[PDB]
Image (cartoon, rainbow, N blue to C red):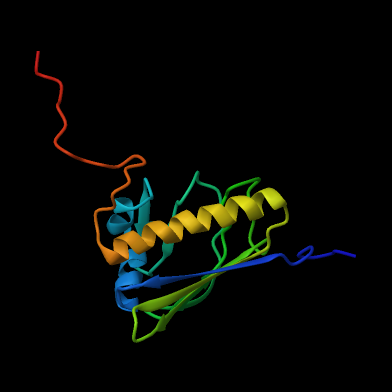
Amino acid sequence: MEKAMPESFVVRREAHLAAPPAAVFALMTDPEKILRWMGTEAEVEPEPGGLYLVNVTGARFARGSFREVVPVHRLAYSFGWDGSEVVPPGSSLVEIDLIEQGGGTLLRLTHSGLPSAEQCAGHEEGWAHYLGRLTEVAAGRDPGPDPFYGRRLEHHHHHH
């Protein structure tokens, strides 16, 4: 009936970036550049040994599980969007692929799993904004939107 990995439900999205594939990887390879567009706390390749991990939301993922790593090319790993319950390893699969093209760079995103419609509708809307925000950075840094971050000469408390 539905033993492991119930149903299928697969979501795929595409986007056109005017920047090369190397620039896109650099953004996901740099923990500080991410804070410029989303991410309140990120840390990658910390102590010797190499370890990619970023807390996109909350702080739940039980244990990491890298499947395949290919810099400036493609990435394969799972962790869930943490948009509901917890989404443990195997419950969903996230993959990002970079393809070089004459007119900008094409980025393909596939997210498998989605055991509930709320996660499907939430992930579809979540990935659209995430991908849309990334395009703004790829086509130009310093995003117009200021969901939380937006430094612009702010006053401060005077000494007393």
Counting from the top left corner in percent of width and height, residue 125 is at 55, 53
Q: Residue furthest left?
A: 159
Counting from the top left corner in percent of width and height, residue 27 is at 32, 65
Name the one closer to the observer, 59 or 112. Answer: 112
Q: Is residue 30 visible?
A: no
Counting from the top left corner in percent of width and height, residue 112 is at 65, 66
Counting from the top left corner in percent of width and height, residue 151 is at 21, 40
How many marks do you count on the picture?
0
Picture quadrant of residue 85: top right
Quarter the C terminus occupies: top left
Q: Residue furthest top?
A: 160
Q: Residue furthest bottom?
A: 102
Residue 140 relative to residue 131: left or right: left
Q: Is residue 8 visible?
A: yes
Please determine whether, in this image, residue 31 is positioned above or below residue 22: above
Residue 117 relative to residue 97: left or right: right
Quarter the N terminus occupies: bottom right
Name the one closer to the observer, 22 or 89. Answer: 22
Residue at (34% x, 86% y) in the render: 102
